[PDB]
Image (cartoon, rainbow, N blue to C red):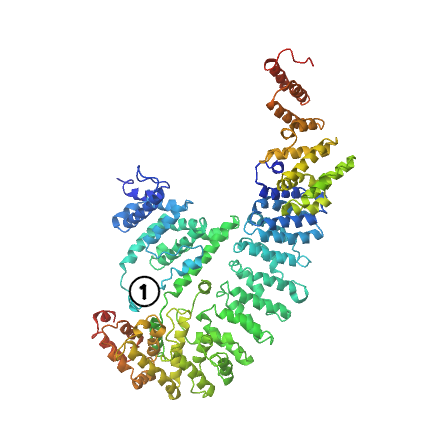
Amino acid sequence: YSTSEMLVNMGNLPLDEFYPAVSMVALMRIFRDQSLSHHHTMVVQAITFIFKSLGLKCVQFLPQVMPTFLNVIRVCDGAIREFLFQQLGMLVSFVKSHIRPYMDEIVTLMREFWVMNTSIQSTIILLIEQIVVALGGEFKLYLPQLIPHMLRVFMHDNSPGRIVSIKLLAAIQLFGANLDDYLHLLLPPIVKLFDAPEAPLPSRKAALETVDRLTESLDFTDYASRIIHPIVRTLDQSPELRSTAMDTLSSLVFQLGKKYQIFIPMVNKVLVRHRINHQRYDVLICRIVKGYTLADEEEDPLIYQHRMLRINLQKAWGAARRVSKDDWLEWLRRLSLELLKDSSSPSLRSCWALAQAYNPMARDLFNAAFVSCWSELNEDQQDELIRSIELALTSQDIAEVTQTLLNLAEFMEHSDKGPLPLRDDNGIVLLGERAAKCRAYAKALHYKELEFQKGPTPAILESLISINNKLQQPEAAAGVLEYAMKHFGELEIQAT
Amino acid sequence: RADVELERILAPYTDFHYRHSPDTAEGQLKEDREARFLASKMGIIATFRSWAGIINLCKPGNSGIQSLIGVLCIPNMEIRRGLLEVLYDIFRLPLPVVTEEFIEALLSVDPGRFQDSWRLSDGFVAAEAKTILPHRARSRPDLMDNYLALILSAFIRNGLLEGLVEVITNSDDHISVRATILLGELLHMANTILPHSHSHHLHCLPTLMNMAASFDIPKEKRLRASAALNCLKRFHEMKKRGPKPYSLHLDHIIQKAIATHQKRDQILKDTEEALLINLRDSQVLQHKENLEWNWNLIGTILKWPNVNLRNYKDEQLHRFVRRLLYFYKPSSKLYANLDLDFAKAKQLTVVGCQFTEFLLESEEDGQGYLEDLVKDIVQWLNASSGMKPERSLQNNGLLTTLSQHYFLFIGTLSCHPHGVKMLEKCSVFQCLLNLCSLKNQDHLLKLTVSSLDYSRDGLARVILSKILTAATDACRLYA
């Protein structure tokens, strides 16, 4: 019932944001059915435009799009799923901190489709980097759920050059301080990668880089002996990794205070044997052997980091060449497409492409499209539209075309701008006799009651009797007669 | 009466809607609540410091303390912040700063933080060293620890530790940080003041650990407690380091003390390749102007194990030292004019003492370069204080400039036996002796006393005796 509420705007939402709301319900209806599977490819490219266009005002639409979007990915199969994930990476980069209620299912959904060796590896990895930026500090709530998949990537990877691992090392650097209770189990996989000679050189390069870049936001004092020893058996082994390995070691001696002093003889023998002369590392070692100050030795690395931080519708309307029923249907479909194209709102413009390939989603958007364009036009332009609607209603007898126009009249009455002008009193007399032949007596009775409120006449009273009888309310019709016996002249009641 | 007279002062904290006066203006209603909270706090503190109030507020039956602790667990935000301030004052603990991160609130509680009484105008070193170096008492009973032990035991028995844990894991982000520090201080207060028996149901955190190991409970809460223990873990390291020196004057006092108690208890080849690569990287030569040299690479060159200008007689090193000699020279106004608050204030000062020690190693050769520094410091002293006829203009600048970090250069020379002999040749001890009898200079006198090293017998001790017996009374008080 909420969906039907929005189509009429019962909440009196201002027209500025009314258009995005009515667009989503039209797009979601064609999104919850598996029968229209082929249209799913291009509908999402329009949803991702609405979210981008609005910005910070798209949060209230999250409870509608997300539950259906997540279900679709679970059931859909083929090339669509790999494309749906990239779109899902965009809707999490727009709304940042409000994806928390829906993150539990997203993490679970990513578990099944992350097959160890498949083309869907990078788009999963690229999605992770977009999620961690969005959460930005509270990712640790869901980080442990994706570590079991990530753990067996540094030892079971058949990609040439171990590119997948490199594409994953650059994603670990973005975690920063998010991982604090998971470093005891995530670091041994990292240190295992740059000590194995059989690993390709580019893979070992990033393994050393991802440690020093992670040093800037984490404390590695406790994990000293675990990663210092692999370093000293790497300088002697690889003559090509000497330059970039010292940068990781030197960035770690800085965190440790005077506790590293006992490790100098173990390292100095590797430096005198292989003649390693690193400029930055030479500075730190001198400061420890011979004193510099007292408030600097044995300093907490986290405190040090904190200190450093601190107009064309007439041709569509005025045709007059439509005589056949199919032409009347064709004219309506031509009109509906034309309104969406130029509706003075990017939210409705984006839906024009889908309207060409799907007509039924343009019928429910007729009311929303009309109010956008009609408001912009002045008195002279909008007057020409009214007289074309008059000719449109009093020409044919097809129920489908009239029902669309009859519903449009009701939509305008509910709005705060008042009903659309017509010949006489917003055309109640014309609409009243127009819905009678369409077998829609709920509207016909309402229009007659408006006529009665102006001035009662014998013709109006007789018509109200006929309408109620065919609406299965004999007792209501009996009240009309009693009104005429005492509140109207005598001996005038027709025997019929 | 029993439980209604004295416990009335606890009403503003236990009652969420307290109305002290039946008739008052509604305009200052918000201000009235804050006034009541402050006044009630001074009464609760005032009744926990008297023996007749502790036994009356901690009765075995229903008491006010169980109502004060029981209200701490209710998820209220205005009461919780008020009660935490009371708890800090009861134990006389330093209050942290309001923040949402633990690191910021940890750097504001360390015992070695700067205070306003440590400046040169106030007590220079004696005030600072009182709160850093420990008291020479290992057997004298501290009668205030006994008082704090009884209060701490009373709160632990009633259930303060369990109440704090609920606060940590079920409150705002800026309230939990104030409660995490209080738990850390209390645990440290309790492993050094409480006896053995009271320490068996203490350092186990039963409530906290169970929450941080259970996967059934909501995920959000689990890591709040896990991170809380992680945040509380770093608190011990801050207490592990202890207070550390803040001023280089006090720092050099400790360094000479540990050196002389470790010298009585009976590294690289440094080929020319290492120096030449390092000297060209120092930037002192090719850019003959300061603020461009790499000040990190200069200290390493000086206190490098084998390079001392004597073993390695090199023309380049003669050029290197003389270029640095011109910068620190007091006459050449390139270093003296620097403001007190220059951003690299520390690094520049340490290297200066780090350099005068380098020259002293080359006793036979460095004395020629060392002769120049000591001479113009004497000339600078002869003008600053005003001992010789001069306008005494340097008095205005001495305080606000780095010219006061010159006693560090002359004090670090007194440590070595061959440095005190150098001072006699330059005759700077004679200059220091005369300036003791100076009425209007008191800033000058204070600096000299602290800088000089009195470990060995010689001229140093004599000058100290004159200062502490023949000078201005205010100056003598500090000596």
Query: Farthest residue in the front direction?
Result: A380
In the rendered image, the residue lying farthest to the right is A324
Left or right of A11, for residue A337: right
Callout 1 amino acid = Thr
Q: x, y (%) of residue A262?
A: 46, 73
In this figure, what is the number of numbered marks? Answer: 1
Q: Nearer the viewer, residue A468 or B199?
A: A468
Q: Which quadrant of the structure image shows residue B390? A: bottom left
**Callout 1: helix, strand or loop?**
loop
Residue B186, placed above or below residue B322: above
Q: Is residue A480 left or right of residue A37?
A: left
Dot 1 crowding, Cα within 10 Å, few <14, some 14–19, many 20+:
few
Residue at x 36%, y 68% (from the top left corner): B246
Give how far across and how far down residue A14 sits, in percent: 57, 40
Name the subunit of mark 1.
Answer: B
Furthest-top residue in view?
A491
Residue B60 drawn at (x, y percent) = 32, 45
Tell me where residue B175 appears, x and y as whole percent. 42, 51
Which image quarter holds the C terminus of chain A?
Answer: top right
Q: Quadrant of residue A331?
A: top right
Residue holding disc 1:
B131
Can see residue A479?
Answer: yes
Closest to the observer: A457 or B294? Answer: A457
> Is A217 located above or below residue B76 in the figure?
below
Quadrant in which the N terminus of chain A is drawn? top right
Q: Nearer the viewer, residue B24 or A126?
A: B24
Asked whether residue A154 is in view, the answer is no
